[PDB]
Amino acid sequence: MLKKKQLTVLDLHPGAGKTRRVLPEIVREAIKKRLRTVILAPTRVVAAEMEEALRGLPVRYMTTAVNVEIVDLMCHATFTSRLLQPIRVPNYNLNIMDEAHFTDPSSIAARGYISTRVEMGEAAAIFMTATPPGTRDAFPDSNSPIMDTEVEVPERAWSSGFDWVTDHSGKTVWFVPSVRNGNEIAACLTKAGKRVIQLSRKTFETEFQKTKNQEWDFVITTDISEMGANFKADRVIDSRRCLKPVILDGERVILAGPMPVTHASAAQRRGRIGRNPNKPGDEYMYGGGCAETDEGHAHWLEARMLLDNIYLQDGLIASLYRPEADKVAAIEGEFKLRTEQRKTFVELMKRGDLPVWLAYQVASAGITYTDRRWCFDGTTNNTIMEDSVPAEVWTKYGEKRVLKPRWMDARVCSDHAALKSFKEFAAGKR
Ligand SMILES: Nc1ncnc2c1ncn2[C@@H]1O[C@H](COP(=O)(O)OP(=O)(O)O)[C@@H](O)[C@H]1O
Ligand SMILES: [Mn+2]
Image (cartoon, rainbow, N blue to C red; front, top):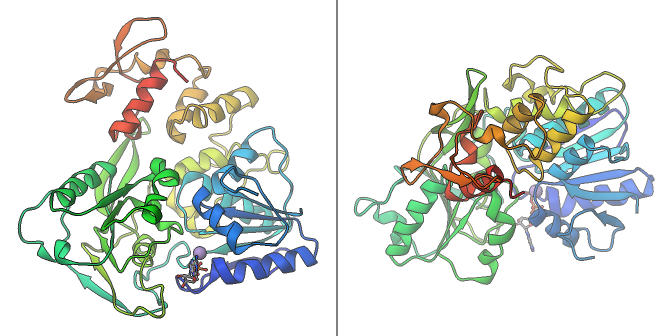
């Protein structure tokens, strides 16, 4: 697997031991061969788990998530961020991506960068995932048999007709299509006397610990838990539905759907259970079919925005990883920014915590990071609502204004927490 100019897809079925058994073997061999190696973990939670699997081995943990060399370990997003910034990144001879199905824009971009370096003959790479891009198998092998049942799954509060949900006496991981939908289901379950933990992208690294430290009956989670999150559960309830960010008329981003998940997403959701060879009969209840909803999904356009701004060699631009390259229609290099606008782009995404697409619109317009006039001078149909009335903030000048951004990205106000963060941004508070 370790030879140069080779990209290996390590696609053992879920729970087969890719992360805990195969990975340390790979690391020991890479150290013996003096290969400069990067290990890419999807989340800080997984990075901390990897330190336990890699205990003893000389690995530099480039994250504060690990309380503790020619092997570096960092998060997917950190790798892509460092490539975008002036910071020097080693030309790693061996690039290991764990949970390489992650569809975050930074993860897609990292796969494009790594796979291009391999294609140029400069490096080796190992992509670890049970569900490579394009998988059509929602029901892969597992360590113990799974009971699969197609069934109508509630997506709103319910009173009758779903007794099977609450009659269960084990622990359930329930994949919902959005934070707001999960809030409603959570409230309904809590009213029925269940103890519920909710997880989403921005709360995961913090709230996941409650699944170890607290008694719980349900974990209500968005698709973030598709990325190596381990639960001691015996049932998965899968709405089989997700929101799809879509760029409309090249001018705005909406959150379309909910709509079907990909086969890979469904397989990863189901793959939370059936992982213990000593506990057969975990249950997977699924509420819809699968479809290729990554086609036209904004994350792959946003990956091209990132990759267009990563230096590879002179003027060349890395391509997306071939199996996922057709999921976006874009002109190669069309998002490349000059030095100063690229710095603004990066700052809008990191400190600004704006979605990639929105950060690009602002930076490519020549706006500097601290200049928030664009948050207020949009068209009337770009007005953002809070509790059914136009949302308002005090500008950094002390004037109360309606939030009406020049470019509208639905992800800045899809839940209360997102809106709170964007209001603070519009006010100049970060
Ligand atoms: N902390 C742990 N202690 C013991 N076994 C674990 C632990 N975490 C995961 N496992 C088990 O180890 C096996 C392999 O896990 P893993 O390497 O994560 O599989 P994969 O990466 O192929 O999905 C699975 O059966 C999983 O349930
Ligand atoms: Mn794994």
